[PDB]
Image 1 (cartoon, rainbow, N blue to C red):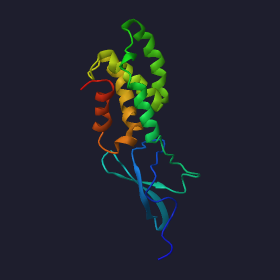
Image 2 (cartoon, one colour):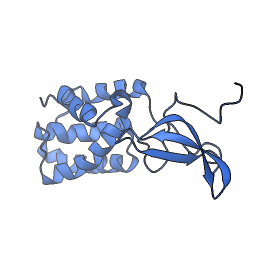
Image 3 (cartoon, rainbow, N blue to C red):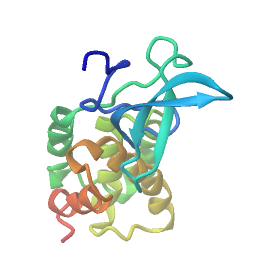
Image 4 (cartoon, rainbow, N blue to C red):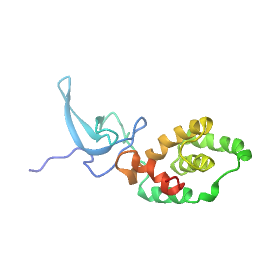
Length: 167
């Protein structure tokens, strides 16, 4: 053959503002009320769903890849120190500087946030108010670190046992 492409086939991960849980598996050609149109075959890593992102409605790109395994390695090193265990007095003040990190959901930030609350209780079963911040941070921990995972959430959720020494 000769012609058999669109924009970018399988080989890059793509993350739009809404989900990001997916990997490019090629381009599918559908028909919108009888019109020839192309879409990125984003294969959802969560359950195996199929999103068809429009290669044209996205304008310039629309779908922007997240951090790479390079970051995932650095991030682990930020939390690998079990000596960050904040005091219960300063903890109330530490809640504030960590509350702002949840707004950004920055990978290097969230990992530090959740870690602080994790070591604050020693185990994963945080208190009512600690679990409230941790629940939002955990949902982002495995979202960014998802790169080194490429599997069930248990991959990153369990990494925390080797980092915070939960076992």
